[PDB]
Amino acid sequence: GQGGKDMLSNGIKYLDVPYVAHTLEADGPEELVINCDEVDCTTLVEYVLAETLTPKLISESAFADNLQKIRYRDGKIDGYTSRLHYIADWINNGVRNGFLQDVTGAMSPDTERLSISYMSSHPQLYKQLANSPENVAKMKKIEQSLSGKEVHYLPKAKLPADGLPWIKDGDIIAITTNTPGLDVAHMGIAFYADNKLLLVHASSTDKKVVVSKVPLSQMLKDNNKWTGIRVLRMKK
């Protein structure tokens, strides 16, 4: 319906926006950072969802408030570890706070048992963990809470090029991975063109936001660490 149309159209506004990693890592205290001109795979989705959730008459204050709700655990900014780094946690936040529906949760009987530990296992890869034993301990606790839970997903072999009727334009796609200790590796926005299910996403290879040149199914097939998808939908 209209919400999916609006998610998609707001995503399309970002075509050609450059890909830049680490845009949220300002030094100093964790605070809301808005950089809509340079995005990564996750920040793209966050800005699109924030805008689409904000009633169009957008209001900067309203946009900011929605972004904060999306990006931080229960919208409460409280250090680096309050940012929802793991997508399973990001999803849980949106479901709990009423602005996401877990579509694969309803529509796919396949499940996986979360095993999340990557960040605390590899703190050298993250500035706010590398020298904060306190943040590492809070990430461990977060990881322990997340792990052991079953979530539904769609295995990649079960996704056709032309999609599935229960995946709709504007849905948020979280690409599941077999990387040890990590649940999700990439994200984007579902877009049907000429009966192919494509992905609008921030591509690090193309260095910008693109419409995928191959269907989402082929994107998954091509990548040996990508296992499938979770499908989430804005609830407004």
Image: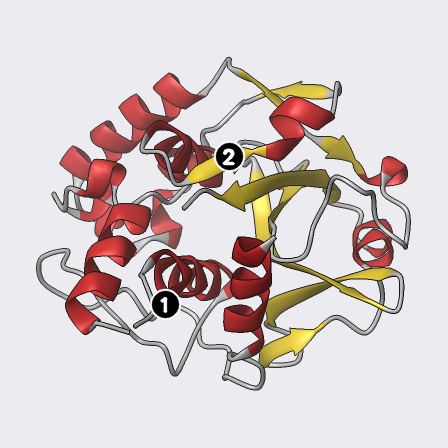
Q: Amino acid at mark 2?
A: Gln
In the depicted view, which residue is nearer to us: 140 or 154? 154
Front: mark 2 or 1: 2
Q: Quadrant of residue 198?
A: bottom right
Callout 2 crowding tier (Cα within 10 Å): few <14, some 14–19, many ≥20: many
Give above or below for 189 relative to 203.
above
* Disc sitting over residue 101 in the figure: 2
Taking the spot 81% from the left edge, 42% from the top edge, the residue there is 165
Q: CA distance from mark 2 to mark 1?
A: 28 Å
- What's the residue at 51%, 79% (across, down)? 14
Position of residue 222 in the picture relative to residue 104 (left or right): right
Percent of width and height locating residue 54 = 31, 60
Q: Do callouts 2 and 1 mark residues in contact (Cβ within 8 Å)?
A: no
Tell me the quarter of the picture where residue 50 sits.
bottom left
Of pointers 2 and 1, the one earlier in the residue sequence: 1
Q: Secondary structure at mark 2?
A: strand
Q: Residue 164: give its label.
A: none
Q: Residues within 10 Å of mark 1 (few under 14, many from 20)?
A: few
Residue type beneath disc 1: His
Q: Position of residue 172 (x, y in %)?
A: 57, 50
| Residue pictured at 66% horizontal, 31% vertical | 104
Tag shown at residue 22: 1
Query: Residue 217 vs residue 32: left or right?
Result: right
- x, y percent for residue 132: 17, 43
- 231 sits left or right of 220 in the view: left
Q: Secondary structure at mark 1?
A: loop
Relative height, residue 131 to residue 53 (above, below): above
Residue under the image location 39 percent in, 53 percent down: 125
Query: Quadrant of residue 113 in the image?
Result: top right
Q: Position of residue 197 (x, y in %)?
A: 80, 58
